[PDB]
Amino acid sequence: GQVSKTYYVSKPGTLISMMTEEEANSITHLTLTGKLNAEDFRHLRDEFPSLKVLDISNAEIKMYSGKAGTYPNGKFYIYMANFVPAYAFSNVVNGVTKGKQTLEKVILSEKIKNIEDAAFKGCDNLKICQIRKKTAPNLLPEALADSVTAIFIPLGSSDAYRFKNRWEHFAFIEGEPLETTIQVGAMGKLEDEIMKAGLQPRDINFLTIEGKLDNADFKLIRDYMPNLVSLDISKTNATTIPDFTFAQKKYLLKIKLPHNLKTIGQRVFSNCGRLAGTLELPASVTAIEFGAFMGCDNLRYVLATGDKITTLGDELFGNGVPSKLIYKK
Image: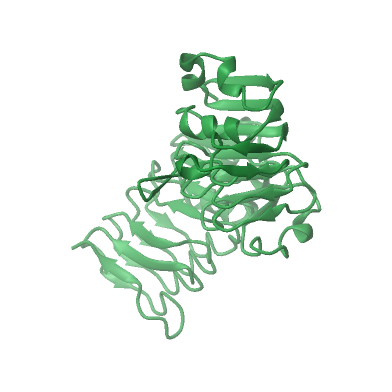
């Protein structure tokens, strides 16, 4: 994207000393090769304010012992070789967890043995952790949040990840992550616009749609996007979400609904078990049809931001489930 740089780090802990502050401040996409240690991670965490994508898949993490690492409050700590260091991108600033909020994607090497305690804790925008290892590295407490980050792993590796301790509930997607923004004109088609972008609908994991969204476009999302992790359709003119649109969405972690949405069809979010906290409804919603949120076990609330709901279908939240519907009123 914006500013892409590649640095070969000859000596671990010397990353920050290889460029100026103005250079490091502008980097959004950083690829590192060579040798790194927890001191480089501290600089990546505390400096590099524009860092969005960190590719360390061809870098080696060397052992470091000292006070210049990522462990909070400058405490002496021993950082093992091939370990994503403890608190790599998480700090504790006067009792408050401060994660690296610009960090959206990390790419780890096949040499990673451990992802240490709280490595990405509070990194609320870490949508991707791509690991080039055929088997899962050890995952330590609070290192990755399965409600936040999707794990991109090599082809045929799902079984060498999903049964490992602390990895059991992550969204695992084999192959490369694909994030895209698609512009759909008033007489256009999402399917045609995806094809013009040189993409395959099935490959899409993080999608932003802007412009026109109709029933045929939603059918493409429903039937040909099984690996959809995040969907942002807020900037679309869709007023209805057809029945079962997000029912077959095993990896769907986040959705931003159309800004002028009126109707949520039947079982639209059926079995969307990864959606959490509060799902905010546009103020224009007037109808939520039969079982729209059945099987959304992790969803705490559905917040109606308007006073326009007049039609609520039956069993919106599943059998015997107390209503999760709340109002901003």
